[PDB]
Length: 197
Length: 149
Image (cartoon, rainbow over all chains, first blue to last red):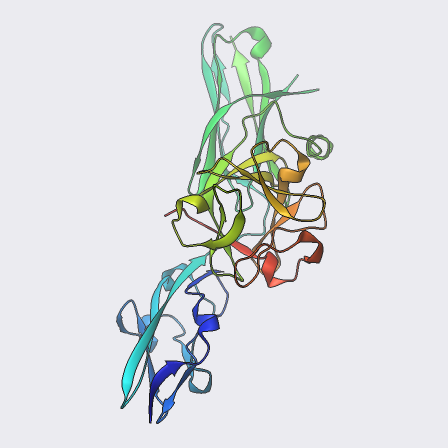
């Protein structure tokens, strides 16, 4: 009587599902047709088996849905629903991106910036590595009463790396230096001492 | 350093290097990415990797206060008094600053700094939503930061 056809292209228009880790992901492909069409799911083009992920998955035929609970990064990929009956077969592919999130204040690498010593006129540097999901701001501070110093740095996929260079050190440069990081949750800071001889 | 940060958090830090992150803003409702077009239009209908969806997010100061700029157009995403998202060449005003929030449901939200009750938001079809109608629990105000492709 009738080939399979999507009954709600609305939800299907949202091909990319980008979600935080620990979320439940539900893919739907509401289908019509007579007789009622059957449905199968593929992951990355091949048969999606229960053993393909920890905790497997669930399918609710009445809702034409694939359900994956507590998704993790290894769940990233393509998921294709194949619906069919005697009059035809159709498919739709969803893409899943899973991102691990953190609702914590910044975390700095222990030991950085490290203490340093140098003879007058010598050069020194201080390094700080900051991990923060929420975009952080970083300040290098000289305990002089605080003086904010301008440093250099680079952004990387999993952390901010900053370095403060102090050239032609003088006795006045001696003292404590702090790397202060903060995001929308809170702050964290590590301090180091510059010894001039 | 609490008092120091409370103080510094009020305005732009003009004495420090300001960190920059580059990514795409995925809209939970639209399934697409935030983009700033040459005609200065802003929406969330861009496919993954669309040049106009590459955003440059520079921190303003502490508290995850940032400015969101379209790398391609060089235009900043700002909000006007009517809660309308507008693209501007000059992004100096507080109206161009947003506080990045990691919601309790683990999604990202961007709250405007000038109008503290308004959030960047888009509809299911990827159209801009007036900040005045935005509340933190609505899916329209939820995003996911995605790596550039």
